[PDB]
Image (cartoon, rainbow, N blue to C red; front, side, top):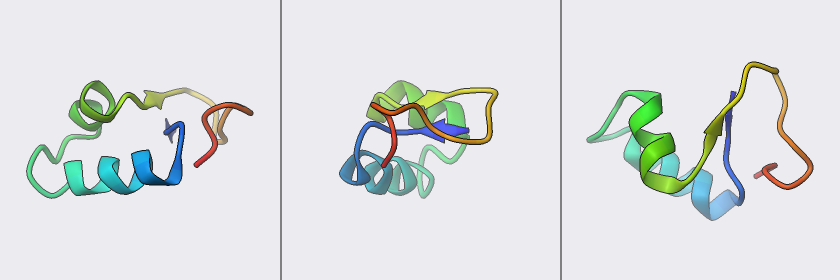
Length: 46
């Protein structure tokens, strides 16, 4: 799960999904963390 530290970072993460499609590129590019759990850390919840 593509846990992003803000709603702007997730919005930017999903614009990352338009060109740099693969979800891991979006993590490397908008400073988000793809984490095994199905929910987000207290400090990385959109």
